Amino acid sequence: KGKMAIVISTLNNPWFVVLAETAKQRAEQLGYEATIFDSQNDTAKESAHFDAIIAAGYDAIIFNPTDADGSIANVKRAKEAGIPVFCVDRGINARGLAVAQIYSDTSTQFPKLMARLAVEWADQYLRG
Amino acid sequence: KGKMAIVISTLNNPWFVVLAETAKQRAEQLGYEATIFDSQNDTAKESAHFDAIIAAGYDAIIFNPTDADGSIANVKRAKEAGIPVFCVDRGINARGLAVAQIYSDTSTQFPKLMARLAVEWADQYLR
């Protein structure tokens, strides 16, 4: 129980709509309240969103960043407020391979959690 | 059911031993057969592991890479063979902070599964 903030870089691109909407739905299925914050590819809007999320005292943040400067600053602010952040994105490697990524500074000491998540992801993929 | 390959960069460090053991246990709990391949910090052995995994027809790969550049080529070969890869690792970011990473060649077009996993990570962290 608690509330999770879903911060998405945009909602005019389908990949991000699916990401934001599915994350909200899964949080609600697990017993959380969840709200989507749309940064609209704007640094100031993303920063304003973190202002409200920190003020509201959300329990966790699912964060799709708009860049690699103001966004890491916003993550730092959430950490100082004691709010864990789990970042989600997709990118293209130097050789062209596209990869979808989840990362977080919270769980580096928890190999059991990371192993279970990776296997559960593979399981959901294979069974569908 | 199915069969997953667990490719670990080394079995000479506790974090990686626990990672590999837990991945094998979780795969079995979820109804899969699982096999561990120890790369022993050797890109040649990692590549040879992917050689045998592709030939054996594994259904999924849980991948802890030895290197950043050379190991991405193994993710390509698996994708070329139609085997989905789910990578788990830890790195040091540009600000010098340790970061835990889970990533895949899947969910780059329809990220429903990755979205759910990110929320489950947060939930398990909170509980």
Image: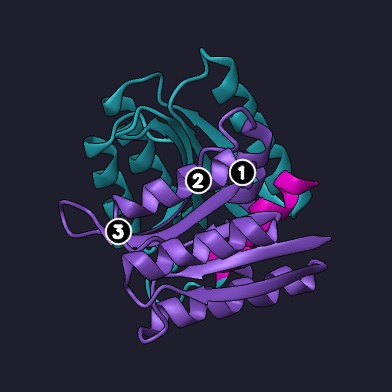
Chain colours: A purple, B cyan
Image depth: mark 3 or mark 2 in front: 2
Name the amino acid type tagged 3.
Answer: Asp
- Residue at 60% from the left image edge and 36% from the top image edge: A107
Residue behind mark 2: A77
- Residue at 65% from the left image edge and 52% from the top image edge: B121
Q: Chain of mark 2?
A: A
Give the x, y percent position of residue B75.
Answer: 32, 50
Q: Nearest the camera: B93 or A2?
A: A2
Secondary structure at numbered mark 2: helix
Would residue A56 be counted in the magenta stretch?
Answer: no
- Residue at 67% from the left image edge and 40% from the top image edge: A113
Relative placement, left or right, of B66 versus A82 is left
For the question of whether residue A125 can be seen, the reply is no
Q: Residue furthest left?
A: A95
Instruction: Indicate the quadrant where residue A100 lies.
Output: bottom left
Residue behind mark 1: A81
Instruction: Indicate the quadrant where residue B112 lies.
Output: bottom right
Give the x, y percent position of residue B60.
Answer: 51, 54
Relative placement, left or right, of A99 versus A106 is left
